[PDB]
Length: 128
Length: 220
Image (cartoon, rainbow over all chains, first blue to last red; front, side, top):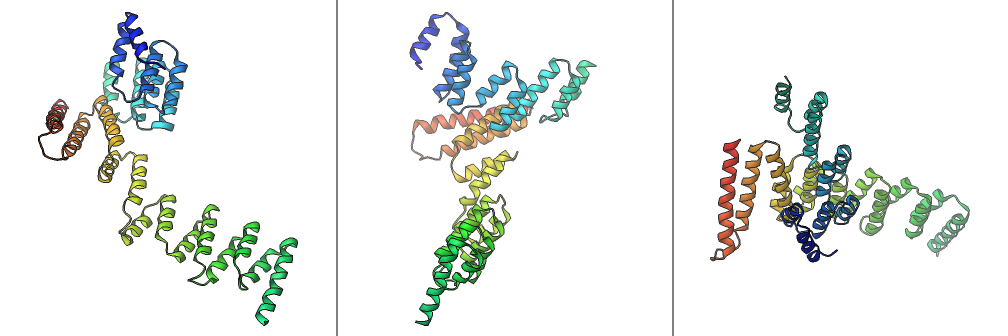
């Protein structure tokens, strides 16, 4: 749990991507969030999850869970913890289904999403 | 002497019944004798709510207030909603009534009680703000938080809502949220009028936010 030596070392990786993550993440009052982000950067997800739970932060953990792939677990976590970004999670799951060419699942999660009047015609004309 | 003799005899009968049994008759006879503490003790031991309610309705108005309050607490902890309501009405204690109303998750009775009690305004509004936050009426939560005064978590969740709106291609809602943010910051400009640099930076940021909202509307 040391930050200054950690950022000096990240400077010494010549790892520009981790430095960019540092720069975009430093605008956060919670240092535990920065530590969890560095844990993601160094590839151990369990430590980042533990740090996020310690700091009582779920939105960043929800974003990480959405990114890694377990969409249903992210939906459950959002609905039982945040419930605010639930519409965003539904939209992201619908977009993932659209990428997977599952038109029925995409339109379904569109009507369960906030907006479906315009997304469905657009995907239907894209598919034809 | 006669009163003392009768009271002593009934107390001895009740004491013998505590060890043996027959709590109903002994308690109901001990209600009209003297002390109410032993009767409530045996009622709690037996959990005989209707007898307790008989005591509450048959007790005098200006002496047994604390006992009625304790009976109301026992009813509430036992989910006896109607008996808690009647005991609170007999108590005429506005604090307990407001607590019961906010615990029962309803507003109409809370609303009429608040109208009847102009000295308690936020005690219902803050739980009302939480209930509004539970639903999708986020703008009403914003206005309630602004009226209350606390805004830091309100500002953070309004920024989250702005990000959600700009992501979901609903640029009109994003422009409205940006206008709300600019208005909140201009309300932060309210502090003093002397030429302090915070005032100038807040004013220029408010101008930038207004321009950003106009760009959101035009792009929408």
